[PDB]
Image: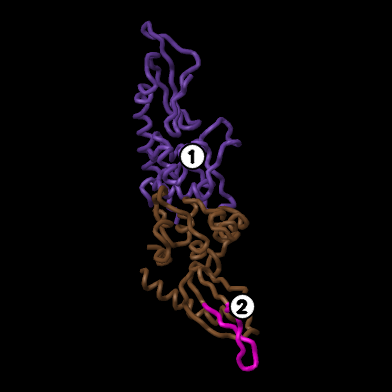
Chain colours: A purple, B brown
Amino acid sequence: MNAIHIGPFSITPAARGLHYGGLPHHQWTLYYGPREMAIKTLPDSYTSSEVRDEFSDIIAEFVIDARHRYAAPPLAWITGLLPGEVLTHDAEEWRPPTSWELRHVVGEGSFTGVSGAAAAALLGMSATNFRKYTAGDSAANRQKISFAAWHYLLDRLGVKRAS
Amino acid sequence: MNAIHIGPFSITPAARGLHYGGLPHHQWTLYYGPREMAIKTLPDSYTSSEVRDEFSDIIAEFVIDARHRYAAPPLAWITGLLPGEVLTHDAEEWRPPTSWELRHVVGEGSFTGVSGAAAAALLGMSATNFRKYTAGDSAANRQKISFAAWHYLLDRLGVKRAS
């Protein structure tokens, strides 16, 4: 496979390839989480960066539509895509973000463009310690960001004021 | 002794008492950290709350003078009393606040009036865990608040915007 992950978006190749014009091909699907966004059949000689370029315009259109739909700090529209329980200031009913929810706001392909190391620096923590927030393959056994650090990070990123 | 601590202020009794009007007396000194603020000789039958009431007006005058001198969030003037290294957003040159600096902003006698348990709730942590930030008698071996939690707390208290 070797799926391509661009923030909260993913591009996945089909299990079984195809053949077109005497060359191997593959059907790639672009998803926003579970939501199927687009499909394109592309040659096998394509680098992953070439596939990312192929789907970048659909991603940018997603961003434009979300900016208009969820119109405050400059990136407040991102809060329209996050569940209320990760945004609430009631710590008793708050829950930490999932990896996908975090990748909405951290990562070069995130909607903020801020890398993991830069976000770690914004929180005063090492990049290796911040990497744990998206590490592993177990949601339940994955390091969770703290309430205070999450809301502080959302303030520093211009997504939601801590107020 | 049994000194009285009111946020960053302390009232200390003299080692050797005195006698006035056939009754035991003690000379109490009110300090703001190391700064001697006032002296009053008061009877031994005074409760600690009575001594606190005796010095409360001088404390309130301190607050008025600081509010005027360090005039933004409503309690921004408190930042005039805190060293720059605990206020800086450069995590590489930041240092955590001391217990005294923390008691500027947390505690019923602090300049915010917000209790330790309420501040803990503002940070999403238990009161017992927050108590560790002012526990013990060793500055070096005292639990330190994190960069993100400290700046988030200062934002939630109305002392300094996280921006």
Depth check: A3 or A61 in front? Answer: A3
Task: Inspect this view and state whether residue A90 appears.
Answer: no
Q: Secondary structure at mark 2?
A: helix
Q: Which residue is mark 1?
A: A130
Residue A2 in magenta?
A: no
Depth check: A54 or A5 in front? Answer: A5
Residue A4 in percent (x, y) is at 44, 25
- Tell us which disc is closer to us: 2 or 1: 2
Q: Amino acid at mark 1?
A: Phe
Task: Inspect this view and state whether residue B67 appears.
Answer: yes
Residue B148 in percent (x, y) is at 47, 50
Q: Residue at x 37, y 5 (%)?
A: A22
Chain containing the residue with disc 1 = A
Depth check: B140 or B81 in front? Answer: B140
In the image, the segment drawn in magenta is B13-29
Q: Secondary structure at mark 1?
A: helix
Main structural element of the magenta stretch: helix, strand or loop?
strand
Outermost residue, bottom direction? B21
